[PDB]
Image 1 (spheres, protein in one colour):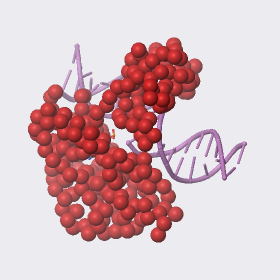
Image 2: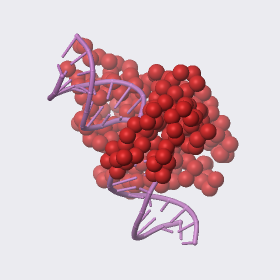
Image 3: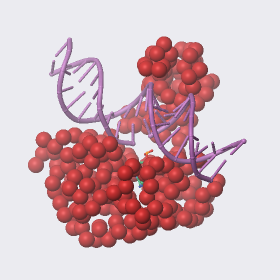
Image 4: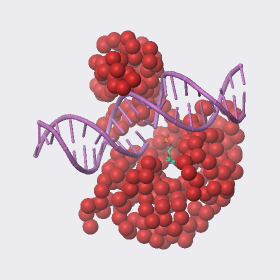
Length: 256
DNA sequence: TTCCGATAGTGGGGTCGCAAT
DNA sequence: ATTGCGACCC
DNA sequence: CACTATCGGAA
Ligand SMILES: *P(=O)(O)OC[C@H]1O[C@@H](n2cnc3c(N)ncnc32)[C@H](O)[C@@H]1O
């Protein structure tokens, strides 16, 4: 019923009281909105799911994360986005981990309660609800994040209990993810496109372990002019690695 | 005063699907 | 059968 | 997804 989607703000952007938030593990899946009749992605591309996958689901609008287990994103994205054309029974171990309803004028605590009500009244086990728990100190958050990360999880999500749904980013829905640093030697330059015409678009870097990947973001516009010369070393941040061990969401930090 | 939230516009890894080879 | 490319997910 | 680079209004 609400127009735009409520996006999640990064943690560092100290001041919040965690006790006022529902905490839940961020599931590295595919976002999907349940139309009551149809599933659709973040940008409203139809998801071609089997009829049994949605059989007996509620007749309401629900936002959820199509998810199997931790560290199964690439495979999950292969099942969900592919057209369905009983072969293509790959949805067997997929679930719809609902986490919110886009209802206007009601606290997330109430929407969560409604979600749990809809699950008990739904015979299909594909319809699930993300587990919501409570933390106290910021230290408790840091330790839980570490544990989840080491256990293969992607991160944590914080949703304010007494907050109403509203599009955009705010402290009502916060996103928590870990990241590490690493070094790599630049092997080549790649010309940028669009506004970065005649400028550096990305760098073919390589890690000491022999993993090569293109580092294409994090540079200021001045850094793109006269970029790190080939043969030098650069430090980049990343959020884990892919199936092929390549850094994910990598961005440039500083040289040396 | 600073800082936040919203846009516009680049870039990656991975995958799917269609056009070109 | 191969390859390249745009458009999506993240 | 990550990011840089603006900009007007909220804090
Ligand atoms: P980006 O991932 O930066 O924005 C957040 C998205 O993550 C999805 N998501 C996955 N798992 C969860 C939970 N447990 N709670 C809330 N959101 C989650 C959302 O679909 C966002 O699009």
